[PDB]
Length: 318
Ligand SMILES: OC[C@H]1O[C@@H](O[C@H]2[C@H](O)[C@@H](O)[C@H](O[C@H]3[C@H](O)[C@@H](O)[C@@H](O)O[C@@H]3CO)O[C@@H]2CO)[C@H](O)[C@@H](O)[C@@H]1O
Ligand SMILES: [Ca+2]
Image (cartoon, rainbow, N blue to C red; front, side, top):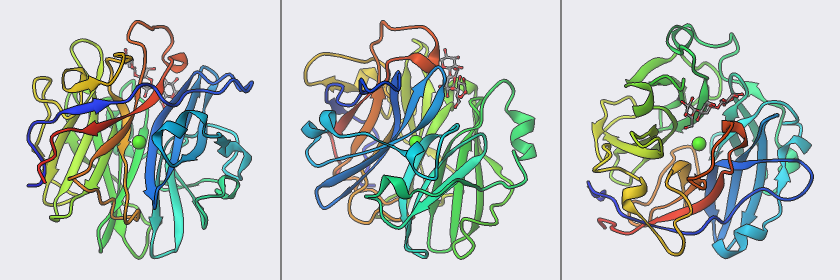
């Protein structure tokens, strides 16, 4: 509607990477990002071969991202252990910020003040009885990953992937959230590489919804596919979801300076304005914080040199 069926982008250079601070982190990854009156708030995965946890950092101008201080959330009650792939939003019924992420289950922490990285609660889980049978049945050799909540004015939905080609969806009422999530349905299914992980589900000003999912291309590089729908529940119609017409991929991203990555991987659209549980974006002014890496690098996945930049949407349709 106010979305083009073809997409073009401009990318920054790699702005955010690990600090030389003794933690040994290899990759900074999987950002969630919101913008409040000039100030960006970011949460990201820390990745290395010993494990994953979470970091917070903030900055106004993008040029200040590289020197932004890292506030590691293992200093909060959120703590040490496995945590990855965060999502932040204000949950207006509770007047608390939620941070959704994975820990082997689907988890959340809350905090009344986004500026306090020490304030994030120890995790609670959306599935207190463990991994749903449907996921156990279909996961194969995959991993349960990349949790995402979006609500409308009646219901809150929790999406997740299995790195095996399923996208799962559970729901509960707005009034019960975070409790009472249903056993998931398979919301969408494809071969592994075509519907792999890193979903985002957004609302649009015209009342429709946008689904982005990360995929692994025939060249082995990460890219994003897209769909729209009239309902969070689907059905989903292709938007830009092929290699020749991608949402974001090496063939529709132009670099300012060097071409520092071929993969366009796990990211989020910068949500400004309301930063609440409706996950509204402005289709006229899309910017996407994403992860990339030197396309010549290899080795163990967990020690890959992931860095964060942004792509800015060049051909807005409004
Ligand atoms: O494209 C490189 C490589 O990707 C592999 O997928 C990665 C996924 O992107 C990643 O989500 C997953 O990460 C898990 C990790 O391997 C585990 O050690 C565990 O502790 O947690 C992570 C899940 O949160 O890893 C896989 C593989 O490492 C594809 O599997 C592979 O085919 C592909 O070449
Ligand atoms: Ca994410």
